[PDB]
Image (cartoon, rainbow over all chains, first blue to last red; front, side, top):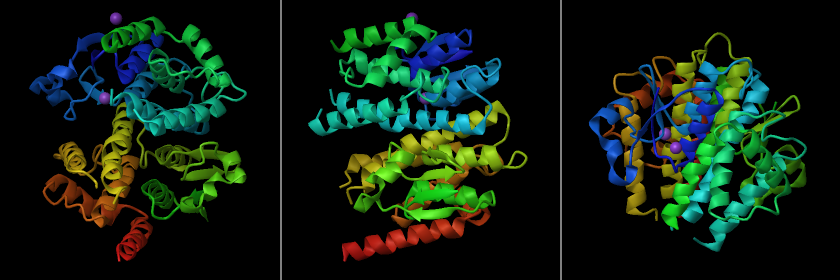
Length: 202
Length: 207
Ligand SMILES: [K+]
Ligand code: NA
């Protein structure tokens, strides 16, 4: 399956980790969006929104990182790995995925993409507080086992770590993060993508 | 099923329409965020993020409008109604839901919440509608040829734009789709009611 991507991006790194966890091979096609490579007509035919990540899986084109992630698990995941069958448990996972996009990652973008006001820094703190509460009394963000929601939020929180946002006062988040780093497949490739992204801005 | 909401909100109205499509009664609990009612400790205990909509279904508290919508369909939907089983068709629906949140509704929020908004933010709306128009090329619905939760969520958003007097008549697939959506989507009447207070409210504040 073809994976149109940039290695530093959080959405791209989420899919990378999910694919590694599922033991799936990605044929990586680096599209430099800083050089408008995502506007090539061959790519636009696959994804008319011409966004990355985009995965092409035997003729099937899908984009939005969190949609890709859930698709790979629903198609290739064995048993209840990373995603259960239960509507209730699945709903919590889905709410955490929208949290990750609309609240947690959104606060990252608002504060670091103007590379940032005190107000937007407060927005990050507020988001981390919610995540900390989400993690009260459980090892993972949506329950008792690693899910796609953990992997997505790891992608985001590791971006914060490398950008040097200090979340050490968030006891649950810090404990979750250390565990997630050890148990999540593909962390090494997440870290590589982050490290270049850091060396980039640095 | 307790439904914590405001009638004007796009996310609240998505849930209202899905609940109607599914035959589900909501016990509506109006939670007015302009008076911090959602910050009250009793609500925070139900939803630590204290956002609306929040659904409490027989002890289970769930929030994020699009998560609530999918939960209702997965738990209560018959057959393949509103959400087919096929991982591929479900994936396209999920992509359209994230589109709705992060691109389409996002462009509404950035332009209209101040109302300033800037010309760049207006352009972002046009860009978002352009993509939606392309998604609808040759297609009756946003994610295939049946009504889905993605249509209902995007209908909530596009109807918000209409009542805010954004002209999308130049997007002819979106316009066609919208006119059809209004006729075939359950709960349209309640969505409109939520919008029209919104208009009347906005109009009166403008003087
Ligand atoms: K690599
Ligand atoms: Na994408």
